[PDB]
Amino acid sequence: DDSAAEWNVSRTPDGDYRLAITCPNKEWLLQSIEGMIKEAAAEVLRNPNQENLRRHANKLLSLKKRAYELP
Amino acid sequence: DDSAAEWNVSRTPDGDYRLAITCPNKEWLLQSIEGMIKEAAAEVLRNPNQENLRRHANKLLSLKKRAYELP
Amino acid sequence: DDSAAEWNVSRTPDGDYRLAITCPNKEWLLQSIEGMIKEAAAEVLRNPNQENLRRHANKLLSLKKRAYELP
Amino acid sequence: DDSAAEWNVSRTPDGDYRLAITCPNKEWLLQSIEGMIKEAAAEVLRNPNQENLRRHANKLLSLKKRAYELP
């Protein structure tokens, strides 16, 4: 239990999906964001008409920067 | 408070770093987890001796499975 | 020389840099192409106005399709 | 007659699958290798007993090193 601590993923009542994870390393977090943005970006290229995908990818881009700028 | 709502990342005392994001699609979440697992794996390949890295990657494997089972 | 056989990367007069690899698995090749497009996509996201990047990404998309069609 | 030039993928009798690509940036090639290594590593984690997978991943690591030194 203490080893897992977090890492929760579920369906929200608002109609969204909630994911809450943790990492004892800044590199792991940065790599995690980097991993998802790359896949996300690929989806955007496959679906140029997908605004939500672009905004989502942009959110990851912002998140990656946020984590990078995080102490 | 109806713009971002989620997508929070900060340093936790017991978890080091806490990331709480959201996605309006299960496919997006699945792709996101896949990205982090990929990077994690690359780290494990470089650090086969890193148990925590394997446990982290394993957590992503579990998370991916969890998201798959999610509605 | 037969030790490596393939897996070569150098400067090509016709393409600047040439990457030549091999894989005895259909999945490995598909995963390889998917890996590069994923990274390439991230570059396109960072440089949306980069036509050559978009074209490059398209080249990967085409390459992936070519590999998909391959027996 | 030769509009493709590069970006070739086919079945080689000497290597099963032959892939030859080009990029005007060394970074792109490095990222390309990184992409395949990431996916490959994930497969290695899924199949730790797969020597060819580990060797393949190592081939990517070696290629990554080669590209890193490549000016």
Image: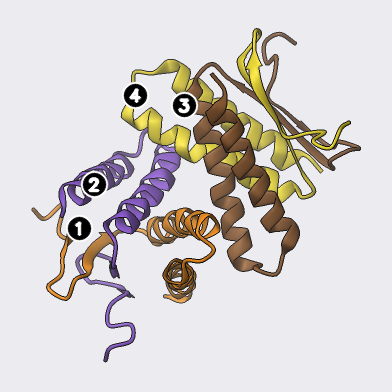
Chain colours: A orange, B purple, C brown, D yellow
Q: Distance between the residues labelled 2 and 3?
A: 24 Å
State the image coordinates of residue C64 (x, y, percent, origin top left). Answer: 57, 37
Q: Residue C39 carries which label?
A: none
Q: On what subunit does the disc labeled 3 rest?
A: C
Q: Do the residues labelled 1 and 3 touch (CB within 8 Å)?
A: no
Residue B45 seen in the figure: no
In this view, which residue lies farthest toward the left? A1
Residue at x 70% of width, y 14% of height: C5
Marks 1, 3: nearer the viewer: 3
Q: Residue A41: where, in percent of width, then height?
A: 51, 59
* Residue A7: image tag: 1
Q: Which mark is residue C27?
A: 3
Q: Which chain carries label 1?
A: A
The answer to which of D52 and B45 lies nearer the viewer is D52
- Asked whether residue C45 appears in the rendered view, the answer is yes
Tell me the distance, in whole angstroms, between the alpha carbons under discs 1 and 2. Answer: 8 Å
- Check if mark 1's residue and mark 2's residue have beta carbons within 8 Å: yes
Which residue does the image show at 62% across and 30% down from the upper left? D62
Q: Mark 2 points at which residue?
A: B59
Q: Is mark 1 on a helix, strand or loop?
A: loop
What's the residue type where badge 1 is placed?
Trp
Mark 4 lies on residue: D48
Q: Are marks 2 and 3 on the same chain?
A: no
Q: Both on one chain, marks 4 and 1?
A: no
Q: Nearer the viewer, residue B42 or A9?
A: A9
Measured in 3D between alpha carbons, the distance from the residue under mark 1 to the one under mark 3, in whole angstroms, is: 30 Å
Q: Residues within 10 Å of mark 3 (few under 14, many from 20)?
A: some
How far, Cα to Cα, is label 4 from label 3? 17 Å
All told, the count of numbered labels is 4
